[PDB]
Amino acid sequence: LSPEDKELLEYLQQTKAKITVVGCGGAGNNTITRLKMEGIEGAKTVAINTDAQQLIRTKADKKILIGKKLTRGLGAGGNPKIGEEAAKESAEEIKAAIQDSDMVFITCGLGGGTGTGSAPVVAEISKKIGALTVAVVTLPFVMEGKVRMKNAMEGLERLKQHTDTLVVIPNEKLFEIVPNMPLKLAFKVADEVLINAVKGLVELITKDGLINVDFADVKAVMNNGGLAMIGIGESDSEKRAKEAVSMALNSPLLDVDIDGATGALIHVMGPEDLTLEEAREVVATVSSRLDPNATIIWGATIDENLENTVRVLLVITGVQSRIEFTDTGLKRK
Ligand SMILES: Nc1nc2c(ncn2[C@@H]2O[C@H](COP(=O)(O)OP(=O)(O)OP(=O)(O)O)[C@@H](O)[C@H]2O)c(=O)[nH]1
Image (cartoon, rainbow, N blue to C red; front, side):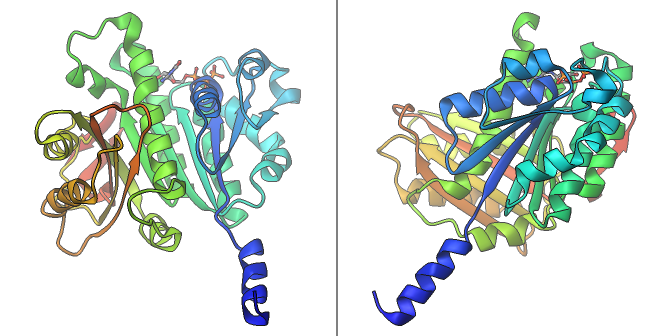
């Protein structure tokens, strides 16, 4: 290299795109374990919990037992205030774990005491250290009771204050995607949706695909993404891409009017035969549903184990104006 280049290269050393995924509580730890095992690209995994038992069986690059003094390696018994206090007690440890992150993804299942209470604290620390802060959480199933939903919605309001983009997945809508879903599989299905949303979002940024995804562009869209919801579709039919995206756009997970969306993140995943043209069609389709002024970030990657199905992850941002937060859940205005 040359003097100019050598300098630049060194610059590239300091600069980067450090991404960290933080799973709080049992549901959050379960998600992290999966990401670590199946291997998530270009991202560090961090699991935190008050419950030492759940944490020890979890798998991640780093684990943080929060609230030692407060809970003594025990769970929060459903009390969000314990999770919040616990996270505060361990702020320094959490800070050390996500310290040099350019972007932090916070994931958990809202409704319990740990995830609900600590997620907002992790988010506050994430922004204070200057990282693009994104949350991807789930709301509980109706069958879990109103207390769990209230605590979740309150935690959702608190989280909303400290995140740059808050992606919310309504577990209850999973029953609209698979009507005859056996209760014993309800959480195994939610698990699948959570992983696809988080891994899908993370890899859209870190995984090499048929087209480059610029981190700066991702920042611009998510810096003020506000409240976001997802849509998931997949098809192996003649018009794989067309059907997949149609499924995503009509997904019950995307429970809101999207015409008033400020932006979107689109991740097209398919087998080795996936072309840029299919991905283009997915994006073209989505763009016609959103405001003509919305910013759309998209990518297309190859998923080794897909065979001949194309999957589409959609993330519509800035829909807070079309949603209302109630103690019973999210309601479309
Ligand atoms: N996908 C998924 N969601 C889960 C699972 N377990 C529970 N949930 C959901 O996540 C919410 C919070 O549960 P946990 O993560 O177990 O709770 P916690 O944050 O650890 O809180 P405490 O046990 O009170 O300390 C529940 O209300 C369910 O909606 C799981 O295995 N997978």
